[PDB]
Image (spheres, rainbow, N blue to C red):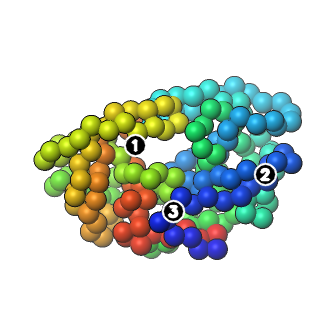
């Protein structure tokens, strides 16, 4: 299956005898699921995201059937606003990004040129918007609140901003604010023709 990014890349998973929908998220190292009944021993853990950190219960060796393919790995269960399948499981079902082809054994980073500055950013299929750490961008901008794993953040919204992603030009809305990592979301990914394959 090859999926485009005009809509959130949602997939049906079966975990612990239960059926759920989850997001194929190349920007997440870990798999994080909403509170659910899982059998076995676990360990408390803390994970960071936009908005901050959340405490999760970690389970190892959990079998998950993602879109009909089986995979075994670590799954985090916690207060996520969405069920996220991270790179730990994505590599197992052979998922790749194509825009070049990129496997997910390492974070999918690219160099972008924006506002005359060079930065590295993460190709993030789980993000609807593009969010960059604080930087010098010209023009008028509007305050906006975006939520994420740790909660929400106020960002400045700039529209019609030119970005050159891995040598591809794209124009769109760019959010500037307190992100821990520069994220290139679906609003720009669909412009450089990014597809997900598994």
In the picture of the structure, the residue carrying the numbered disc 1 is: 181
Mark closer to the observer (2, 1): 2
Label 1 CA crowd tier, 10 Å (few <14, some 14–19, many 20+): some
- Snapshot quadrant of residue 146: top left
Q: Secondary structure at mark 2?
A: strand
Using the image as rendered, state which of residue 19 and residue 71 is in the foreground.
19
Q: Secondary structure at mark 3?
A: loop
In the image, taking residue 133 as reference, residue 50 lies left or right, namely: right
Look at the numbered discs 2 and 1 and tell me whether their residues touch, using CB distance below 8 Å. Answer: no
Residue at 36%, 69% in the rendered image: 191
In the picture of the structure, the residue carrying the numbered disc 2 is: 19
Q: Quadrant of the C terminus?
A: bottom right
In the picture of the structure, the residue carrying the numbered disc 3 is: 7
Q: Is residue 147 above or below residue 124?
A: above
Q: Position of residue 15 (x, y in %)?
A: 80, 49
Q: Secondary structure at mark 1?
A: loop
Q: Position of residue 71 (x, y in %)?
A: 77, 56
Q: Position of residue 53 (x, y in %)?
A: 52, 28
Q: Quadrant of the N terminus?
A: bottom right
State the CA–CA distance, disc 2 to disc 1: 32 Å
Q: Position of residue 85 (x, y in %)?
A: 64, 51
């Amino acid at each position: 299956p090859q999926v485009t990014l005009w809509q959130r890349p949602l997939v049906t998973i079966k975990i612990g005898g239960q059926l759920k929908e989850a997001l194929l998220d190349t920007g997440a190292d870990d798999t994080v699921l909403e509170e659910m009944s899982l059998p076995g021993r676990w360990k408390p853990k803390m994970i960071g995201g936009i908005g901050g950190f959340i405490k999760v219960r970690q389970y190892d060796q959990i079998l998950i059937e993602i879109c009909g393919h089986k995979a075994i790995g670590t799954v985090l269960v916690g207060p996520t606003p969405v069920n996220i399948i991270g790179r730990n499981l994505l590599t197992q079902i052979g998922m790749t990004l194509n825009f070049p082809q990129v496997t997910l054994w390492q974070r999918p980073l690219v160099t972008i040129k924006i506002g005359g500055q060079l930065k590295e950013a993460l190709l993030d299929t789980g993000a609807d918007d593009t969010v960059l750490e604080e930087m010098s961008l010209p023009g008028r901008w509007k305050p906006k609140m975006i939520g994420g794993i740790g909660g929400f953040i106020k960002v400045r919204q700039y529209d019609q901003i030119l970005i050159e992603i891995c040598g591809h030009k794209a124009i769109g809305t760019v959010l500037v604010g307190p992100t821990p990592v520069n994220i290139i979301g679906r609003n720009l990914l669909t412009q450089i023709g990014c597809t997900l394959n598994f």
